[PDB]
Image (spheres, coloured by chain):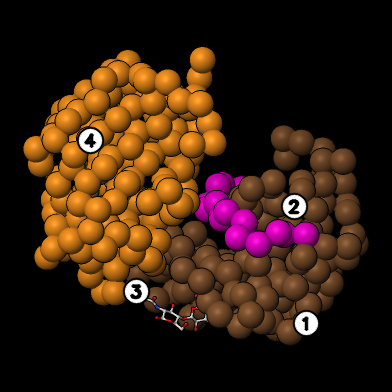
Chain colours: A orange, B brown
Amino acid sequence: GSMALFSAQSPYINPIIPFTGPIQGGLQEGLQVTLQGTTKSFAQRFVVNFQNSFNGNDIAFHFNPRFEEGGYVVCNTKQNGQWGPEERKMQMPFQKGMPFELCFLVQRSEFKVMVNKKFFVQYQHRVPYHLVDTIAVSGCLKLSFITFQTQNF
Amino acid sequence: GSMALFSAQSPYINPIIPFTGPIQGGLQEGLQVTLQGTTKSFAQRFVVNFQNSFNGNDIAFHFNPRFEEGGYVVCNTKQNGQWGPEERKMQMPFQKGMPFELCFLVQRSEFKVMVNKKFFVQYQHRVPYHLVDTIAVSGCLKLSFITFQTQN
Ligand SMILES: CC(=O)N[C@@H]1[C@@H](O)[C@H](O[C@@H]2O[C@H](CO)[C@H](O)[C@H](O)[C@H]2O)[C@@H](CO)O[C@H]1O
Ligand SMILES: CC(=O)N[C@@H]1[C@@H](O)[C@H](O[C@@H]2O[C@H](CO)[C@H](O)[C@H](O)[C@H]2O)[C@@H](CO)O[C@H]1O
């Protein structure tokens, strides 16, 4: 790509869904988390959660495509079990049955989310990203890799 | 506020709604456009448009509170008369019948929107903001003023 990237931790390969796993050392500015997978042919919804610990009470960033009402994506944060105000992008960048690349870039003030190489949505951090130590993926997809890379030398 | 602010263009004081007027010289990085006003007691919707010319066909940033379905705000861009994909924040930071301060900060890659001095939404620039030379405000509100300020 347009930036030199270096491995952080090692990839999750054909991780079975639902998948929960560590983000080693926590999210860090300049980190890129890329999921490569396929939206299932009769997909209704799927979920990527960047969370603090395993119980899902505290999800810094919930990313939830919904193949409903024309197709839209919900982004939100859960704190002490409580969902905050949703940010809905009224567009569906995934296609049922089709492969996708979904990349999450951690910046100082926001996540930037690309789908198939194109900017899709920004999400302002509501809670500290460094406290996210877990990724959880569930729903109507399959995945061939999750990789973790950084631009930081 | 936490930083000294200086006028960039004189205010529009008590502008009559619907209001359309110049943003003299176009939007600039670092400009803050502040609307001080009151949401009407039975508001349905109101609109703040940052647009290129009087026409309305090209709206860089359409900011549209809707007192509908629990309350939500629509952000979008219009290009050649066509609406792009809506960004909806499913929260209503305005109260019907109540004063508000609504502040748009032009940053290099996004607008930042503050409501009553709290961050409300960000909106990534889809077209260069400097082509915006016109503000249009309409709907269920009144304004005491619109100011244009910079940290300058
Ligand atoms: C219109 C509206 O606000 N709808 C919401 C639902 O989106 C919400 O569903 C939950 O949403 C969260 C993220 O906010 C997460 O995706 C949950 O899986 C999902 O069930 C619902 C219940 O919280 O409230 C509705 O009214
Ligand atoms: C759920 C959905 O996508 N609904 C949209 C409406 O929001 C839209 O209404 C228009 O929205 C634009 C900004 O996007 C502007 O606020 C107009 O005043 C409003 O009429 C409608 C027509 O474009 O499409 C619906 O599908």
State whether label 4 is within 8 Å of ligand 1.
no
Nearer to me, A28 or A54: A28
Return the residue found at the far front: A1
Badge 3 residue CB within 8 Å of ligand 1: yes
Q: CA distance from mark 3 to mark 1?
A: 31 Å
Query: In this orientation, which residue lies closer to the viewer: B49 or B56?
Result: B56
> What is the chain letter for disc 4?
A
What residue appears at the point 35 percent right and 60 percent down from the top-left corner? A93
Q: State how many labels appear.
A: 4
Residue B85 is situated, as x and y percent measured from the top left of the image, at: 46, 68
> Which residue is label 2 attached to?
B32
Q: State which chain disc 3 sits on.
A: B
Local packing at callout 2 (Cα closer than 10 Å; few below 14, some 14-19, many 20+) is many
- Amino acid type, residue under disc 1 in the picture: Phe
Whether the residue under disc 1 has CB within 8 Å of ligand 2: no
Q: Are marks 1 and 4 on the same chain?
A: no
Q: Quadrant of residue B123?
A: bottom right
Asked if the residue at tag 4 contacts the one at tag 1, i.e. Cβ–Cβ closer than 8 Å, the answer is no
Q: Which residues are magenta?
A: B113-130
Determine contact: label 3, label 1, CB under 8 Å: no
On what subunit does the disc labeled 2 rest? Answer: B
- Mark 2 or 1, which is nearer the eye? 1
> Which mark sits nearer the N-terminus, 2 or 1?
2
Which residue is denoted by mark 4 in the rendering?
Answer: A145
Q: Secondary structure at mark 1?
A: loop
Mark 2 and mark 1 in contact? Answer it, CB < 8 Å. Answer: no
Residue B131 is inside the magenta segment: no
Mark-to-mark CA distance, 3 and 2: 30 Å
